[PDB]
Image 1 (cartoon, rainbow over the protein chains, first blue to last red):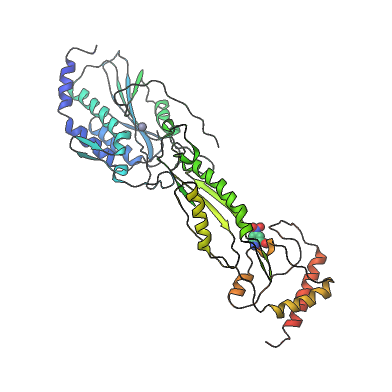
Image 2 (image 1 turned 120 degrees about the vertical axis):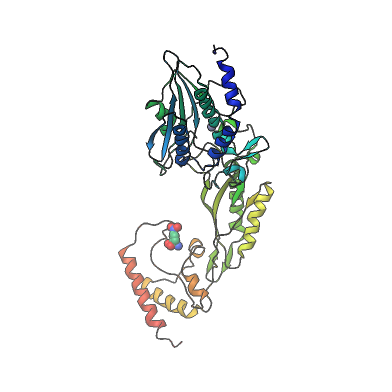
Amino acid sequence: MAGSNDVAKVMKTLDGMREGLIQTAVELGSIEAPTGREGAAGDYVYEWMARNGFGPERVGVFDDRFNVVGRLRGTGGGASLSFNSHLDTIMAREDTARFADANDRIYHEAWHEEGRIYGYSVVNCKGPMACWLIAAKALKEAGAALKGDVVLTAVCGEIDCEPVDEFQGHDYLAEDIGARYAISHGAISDYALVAEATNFKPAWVEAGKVFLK
Amino acid sequence: VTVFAGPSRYTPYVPRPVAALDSPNAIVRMAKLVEALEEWADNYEKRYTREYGGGTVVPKVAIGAIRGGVPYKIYAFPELCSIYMDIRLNPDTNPLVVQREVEAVVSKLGLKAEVKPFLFRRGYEAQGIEPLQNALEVAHREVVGRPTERPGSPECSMWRDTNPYNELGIPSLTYGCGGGAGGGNTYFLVDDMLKAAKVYAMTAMDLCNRTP
Ligand SMILES: N[C@@]1(O)CC=C([N+](=O)[O-])C=C1C(=O)O
Ligand SMILES: [Zn+2]
């Protein structure tokens, strides 16, 4: 494994998808999606998945803050693999309390230039998301032979915001309604690759946290 | 007073160890500034103490509030942090002089801060108070039995609505029963209250029968 040169066909198919890759990343990256308002980004991904025949479902605690889960169904008898990236981004309409420069173009937009794609929302995390969205599209369209399912999981509320004191509920929740919620309500698989910007370096330990008032 | 620092980092990337005044975390810098301003405040009230006919003003300073970052997003420390200072002025002190003094405390620490006034009101010594002062004195000696004592400094060094009256050319003094809430006291003797009402009524019967 993997395959024979079933691989070669898929690699060429991906070569031919370079424009889709850039387009998806720019469009996704251009959507305003600070934690608390990921809905519009979610909708984009849902429709993208629907268009491409991945039978997406919105899986969320709130109707405007939800995870999106689709699948490329395998033929049977293989391990399933989830691809996962998050829908929310860092800087809200105005985080003047955190950052002194809470409004630069790079902080709230995304665009294709040279052979680059600019924008914090691309780095974190619409770019890696576009990557496996395209990967799945290629696998599907190349007719790749897969015994196991590929599960496509775009999650809300990855960023470390949390309710506390008088700041409660819908507007301030994050991780509790994101990935763990999506998995607990059906987005399960044998393995999961979380796509984030790591410069092609794999990690498989992470920290926990305790917040103290 | 808003101290600047930064750049902000996601907690797993925060640079340590850093000296407090050099902390990229504005909160940590503000902590040093708070201490220097407390030192400044101790001396400020001494330096600007001033005796008037109407009382001795001991103008005090307190830090009444602080905020930096927001509680519901604490994964990246803030690049700015603000305190809100209550600085009393004797009647002869320009607010700008005080602003400069605070700016100097900041500068000596080598910090960058914005020092912004968001409130200024003047204090006043009454002028031409004598006819009310006298009517009151006579009433007080009669009802209470002894001459009036000069007020403690705190009660001469606060906000009271004598300021707007005096500002507008209406000589005005403050007087009543009980120790002061800011102190703070928690009850009145009914007896004292009655002495106050009688002092007030007598003051009026004197003063309002004098020709203006
Ligand atoms: N001038 C005030 O009314 C305003 C506020 C308080 N206080 O901060 O307790 C006290 C006053 C007082 O001397 O009664
Ligand atoms: Zn991320």
